[PDB]
Length: 475
Image 1 (cartoon, helix red, strand yellow):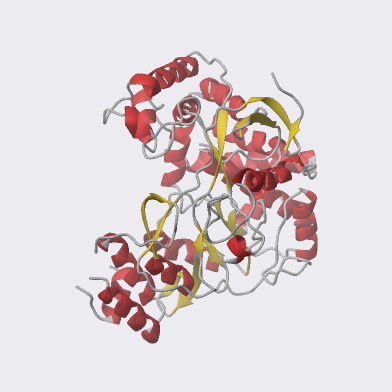
Image 2 (image 1 turned 90 degrees about the vertical axis):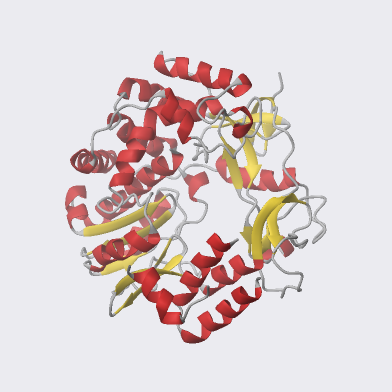
């Protein structure tokens, strides 16, 4: 029945999480050595041969601290109110009304390759028949669904984890850092997917017309989305640091009012929503801690986080320019995917005050240069980035071009089963991935593609440069 603080946060109970994984899924594609510049998978803990560093638990503690930090301020009530209304008005106008989700659809929509979280901590497939859940997950899922249909509350229990992904060298060999993941429990996933799966489908259908850019295909949808943005005189990217842990529950509650209101079973979704926003129970292994503020990375949450982003951005804009939110929306094009943003506007936005305002809400915008100061607006869209592609304009139009280093990386590394040493190579010589690479290399001109296609060829239908450029850009 423990007590006290763990990493600045109140302890609620003993934890049930199994230990943090010390394994990576990335494998080198060749045995050849790697320059000291190259990205490698994030730190693997005590057992990590590359560097003797701190414990994984220590690394997670360092991630949890920002959630203990004092919130920034709320935007002035009247602005928050007018922004929330304007946003949800916009969505009422564009969103196609939906059928409620069944338990069957909810269960289908779940990613079967990830852990079911508390209490069973098991890969979802392991109890999946192909069309239903059985055994343990079947019970948990059947239970969660009854509570959801009854409008009864259930406390989510997230399982803390650290992201296995490629990071730049100083994250491994300098100050070691690893991204915190919140793994929802199955019951929560089922309740959230019934409540809000409709909103998500509806929202996915309008990824071109609305600023929540989730669902967008970079190749097919990119050039339209960018052309839209190019109609506006000024363009910017706030590029936030620690978005998730700086969120305010008060802002997320407004985002959640919107989702709820626009759902086909709003009384049922209300309960789920309130459950998702109540102080979060996080299992860090030793303990389950209560985290009252910030955003939980677990479950829908990508849309809730984009809504919140839209709310925040529009508040700063309304505050500085004094223009009504729906008018700001008339004179503006926004792109959001959680923390990621492009904002284009015809309005004469004061950058110093816009930045002041975002910092006042407790957000941490950052400059391109990494120097302190006001946010920078440009009169060209070229240069601004979104979803890891750089936005380029040419005689034929606007497109998203992934940078060289991202492409090089996908050559150097591949996914496989979990293992302890990232440099061990995978025996056996992935064409689906190899195709899309050649595509991305095409957008970079003559010299670069010819050195990529060379490497690709060594990994043993590889056409000419302009013959794939035209494929990936147009038909």
